[PDB]
Amino acid sequence: DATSELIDKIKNIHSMTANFNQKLIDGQTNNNLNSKGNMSLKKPQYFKWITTSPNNQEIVSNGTKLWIYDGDLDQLIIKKVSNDIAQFPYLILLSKNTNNINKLFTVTAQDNNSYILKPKNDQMIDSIKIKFTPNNQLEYLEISTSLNQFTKIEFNNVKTDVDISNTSFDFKAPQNTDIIDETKF
């Protein structure tokens, strides 16, 4: 029921770009940490998350490689992509059916077009809240974790059904980047 309503909204986001503002509330340090940036998404497997302030970071996935770039360290970690929706909330936003979500999460619908996902077996994530605007646009994500951290990500300047070329999601390292390639066999 609730899972089906959520996926109907997600499956209809074929591509998207947006700005984001992130506030991270850390209970173990009692620090409130702010950041901002932009994101791009394209079904079925493309995701890009760029932090522009205060740090420079990029997470990019093309369905084959996951690139984790820290601009302040000039360091790149490369991993293989798994459809690990329990670990990566943004993979929920690429979903097209309810099969794996229902096996890994209990999903509840609430008023004002929001949904709460609670893992059935997970220690890291306590809950994921996905909120849509009345006209079914992505509005914010809230992620609560057993590290006692609460992350709220709010989207603005949302644009959908842009035509992003697939090469936009193939990361090209800057010159002299420190590489940790974890895909080598």
Image: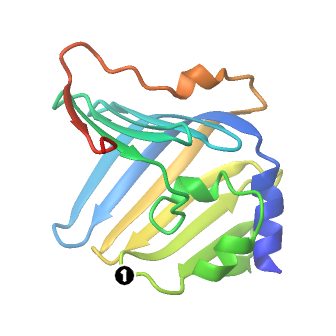
Q: Nearer the viewer, residue 104 or 156?
A: 104
Residue 105 is at least partly visible in this image: no
Residue at image point 29% right, 30% down: 56
Which element type, helix, strand or loop, lies under badge 1?
loop
- Residue picked out by circle 1: 123
Residue at image point 30% right, 45% down: 185
Residue 101 to residue 38: above or below: below
Q: Nearer the viewer, residue 8 or 144?
A: 8
**Residue 60 appears left or right of 14:** left
Amino acid type of the residue that numbered disc 1 sits on in the rendered structure: Gln
Residue at image point 71% right, 41% down: 43
Q: Nearer the viewer, residue 7 or 24?
A: 7
How many callouts does the rendering have? 1
Screen quadrant of the N terminus: bottom right
User: Residue 137, image x and y in percent?
Assistant: 74, 48
Q: How is the image coloured?
A: rainbow
Query: Quick one: which residue is furthest to the top in this view?
Result: 175
Residue at image point 62% right, 63% down: 130
Density class for disc 1 (Cα within 10 Å; few <14, some 14-19, many ≥20) is few
User: Residue 15, image x and y in percent?
Assistant: 72, 36
User: Residue 20, image x and y in percent?
Assistant: 50, 40
**Residue 67 appears left or right of 75:** right
Residue 182 is at least partly visible in this image: yes
Residue 36 to residue 163: above or below: below
Residue 128 to residue 45: above or below: below
User: Residue 156, image x and y in percent?
Assistant: 60, 38
